Amino acid sequence: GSPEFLGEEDIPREPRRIVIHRGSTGLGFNIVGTEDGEGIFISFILAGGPADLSGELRKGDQILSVNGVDLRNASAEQAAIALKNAGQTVTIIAQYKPEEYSRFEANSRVDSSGRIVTD
């Protein structure tokens, strides 16, 4: 009757396992991080790329590990090398951390429903 919007439902904050299958051109997402290793976050998912095709990753996810390699304290450069080298079947542990992510993206913030919005 009244429509049931997904946007009015909380995005799960618990860690998840996601398997991504490499395309001809990589995994179809970009990351941001720091040289001190304060987290690796998905900043962008390419429409139609492997990450998108999984249906299980979003901007603001922190990549905790790749194929069992702990990336919680890695630089973006280290993370990029790990992801490159991860082979054709890539097992990611991710966790949605929009507040932490929002500190990286200019003019962004987290709304009442836990979504990242940019002004």
Image (cartoon, rainbow, N blue to C red):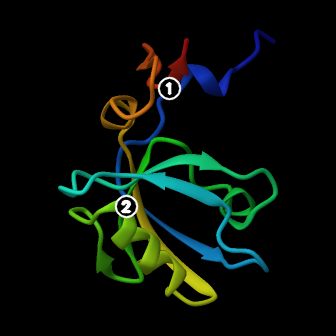
Q: Position of residue 51 (x, y in %)?
A: 65, 62
Q: Which of marks 1 and 2 is nearer the N terminus?
A: 2
Q: Distance between the residues labelled 1 and 2?
A: 21 Å
Determine whether 59 is above or below 50 in the image. Answer: above
Residue at 72%, 52% in the rendered image: 46
Quadrant of res 1: top right
Determine whether 65 is above or below 45 in the image. Answer: below
Left or right: residue 52 compared with residue 105: right
Q: Name the residue under label 2.
A: 76
Determine whether 44 is above or below 80 in the image. Answer: above
Q: Where is residue 2 in the image (x, y as percent from the top left)?
A: 76, 9
Left or right: residue 9 compared with residue 28: left
Q: Mark 1 points at which residue?
A: 116
Residue at 55%, 11% in the rendered image: 119
Quadrant of res 69: bottom left
| SS at mark 2 in the image | helix
How busy is the neighbourhood of tag 1: few (under 14 within 10 Å), some, or many (20 plus)? Answer: some
How busy is the neighbourhood of tag 2: few (under 14 within 10 Å), some, or many (20 plus)? Answer: many
Residue at 42%, 83% in the rendered image: 67
Query: Looking at numbered disc 2 in the image, what kind of residue is underneath it?
Result: Ala
Q: Give the foreground label among 1 and 2.
A: 2
